[PDB]
Image (tube, coloured by chain):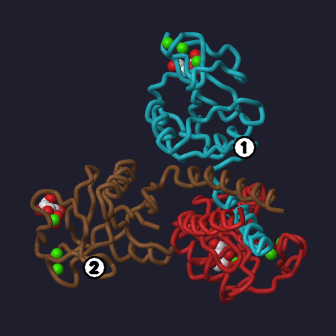
Chain colours: A cyan, B brown, C red
Amino acid sequence: QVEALQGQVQHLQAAFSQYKKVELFPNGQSVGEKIFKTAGFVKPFTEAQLLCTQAGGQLASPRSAAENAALQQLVVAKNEAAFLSMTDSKTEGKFTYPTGESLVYSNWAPGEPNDDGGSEDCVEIFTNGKWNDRACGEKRLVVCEF
Amino acid sequence: QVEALQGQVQHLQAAFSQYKKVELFPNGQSVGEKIFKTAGFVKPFTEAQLLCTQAGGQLASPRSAAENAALQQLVVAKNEAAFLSMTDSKTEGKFTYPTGESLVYSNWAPGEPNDDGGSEDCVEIFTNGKWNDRACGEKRLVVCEF
Amino acid sequence: QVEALQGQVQHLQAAFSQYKKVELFPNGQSVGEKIFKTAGFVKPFTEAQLLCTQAGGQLASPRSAAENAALQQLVVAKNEAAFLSMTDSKTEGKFTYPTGESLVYSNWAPGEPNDDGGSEDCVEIFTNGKWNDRACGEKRLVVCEF
Ligand SMILES: OC[C@@H](O)[C@H]1O[C@H](O)[C@@H](O)[C@@H](O)[C@@H]1O
Ligand SMILES: OC[C@@H](O)[C@H]1O[C@H](O)[C@@H](O)[C@@H](O)[C@@H]1O
Ligand SMILES: OC[C@@H](O)[C@H]1O[C@H](O)[C@@H](O)[C@@H](O)[C@@H]1O
Ligand SMILES: [Ca+2]
Ligand SMILES: [Ca+2]
Ligand SMILES: [Ca+2]
Ligand SMILES: [Ca+2]
Ligand SMILES: [Ca+2]
Ligand SMILES: [Ca+2]
Ligand SMILES: [Ca+2]
Ligand SMILES: [Ca+2]
Ligand SMILES: [Ca+2]
């Protein structure tokens, strides 16, 4: 019996692993325990944020070079800059994750963030992986993390 | 062995939970034990019906307000009215599920169904969640349930 | 604690089966233990091949009439001819899989392969399921197998 349950769990592990690859192709990227997935279209920050939260996740929040590289692959594939989850909407000059925590990693392009026009509280990631603070009202690729 | 086998099932459960969220974003919606998934494009009723059946499911068949609201979320997201599986092709005035049973739930807009032009045997759901009988030849968003 | 796990596995099995069908709709097709999935866009051969390999799979490689029929379903649904993995880049006239192994199945359209222009080393599958050797530089629907 204990062995009969083995044959099942074993089959499940194999089937699940195959299904995982299928699911991630071509809009997902796995990095560590995190999975990034793009919706394939653009939206303003507030709408992008809501879409990810309702899906049980949150906007892409790269916390390391490895995660940022994984996210970058999606941006390049779609050739569309994407929104990150971080903003300095609460306190200008201080970017935070949705929880309020301060950034543990950043990859700002030279000179950024610069709050251009005194109205850039959101963050976009370019095809080169670099970050730029941009107006939250702009529309960018929606990428959520799970 | 149980000790280790429990660790495997626990890993599968956790991994699967994550992947379910990933899979449903952004074209799926879970409600109870039913899952709605949109193909993202429009098709006439017959073509839409065949796509769903060949995929191992059937056209969206909301049987409760909760299921209807879940379906509505997809229709709103794609901003395209979708076909439901029910029709009154067999007997005019009596809408049934693909199996033949009569409806157990309905959310008709006022005055519907009205068999306009004496030729509306299919059903579409609007972005406001209401139903309208419509010509089966029209093209509407394809949403299947599994 | 035995019946405990057995219960969880059965239910995990059922949930996985449902998510499998949801996953394949509308861009995937399962045949045997193989799964075909289209990216939904076209790319030149090398780029397409790279996308599949990086995803942990490879370009569509139908090895039987059954596999070819399943692949043809996706080509028909997308209405776009797709690249297969096989090429005769090494030895003109001799088509092989990425491993170097010779074909074990083929469905060449009448008059094919003809190496037209003296430079057609890749293979495409039409909506009718037939194959045609085509210049690897052309762009065709990307379909991987897992
Ligand atoms: O609204 C200004 C933006 O379009 C960007 O213009 C220039 O690239 C730089 O000033 C950026 O920092 C700014 O976000
Ligand atoms: O064929 C007529 C339809 O386009 C719809 O026209 C009006 O909105 C109402 O008569 C509807 O009931 C009808 O389905
Ligand atoms: O470059 C020519 C291709 O477009 C194909 O056109 C026709 O299908 C046939 O001549 C094929 O052999 C050719 O590869
Ligand atoms: Ca500000
Ligand atoms: Ca700012
Ligand atoms: Ca800026
Ligand atoms: Ca009628
Ligand atoms: Ca009618
Ligand atoms: Ca009507
Ligand atoms: Ca050649
Ligand atoms: Ca050739
Ligand atoms: Ca040819």
Q: Is residue B48 left or right of residue C63?
A: left
The residue that mark 1 highlights is A33
Residue A95 image-quadrant placement: top right
Q: Is residue B49 left or right of residue A74?
A: left
Position in image of residue B131 (x %, y %)? 22, 60
Using the rendered image of the protein, determine whether residue A4 is visible from the camera's viewpoint: yes
Q: Residue at x 28, y 68 (%)?
A: B138
Rendered-image quarter of ligand 11: bottom right
Q: Is residue A21 left or right of residue C118?
A: left
Q: Observer-nearest residue: A116 or A6?
A: A6
Q: Chain of mark 1?
A: A
The residue that mark 2 highlights is B101
Q: Residue at x 61, y 46 (%)?
A: A37
For the residues marked 2 and 1, what is the alpha-carbon distance in whole angstroms?
A: 46 Å
Does residue C18 lie above or below B26 as drawn? below
Position in image of residue C78 (x %, y %)? 53, 68
Q: Chain of mark 2?
A: B
Position in image of residue B141 (x %, y %)? 36, 61
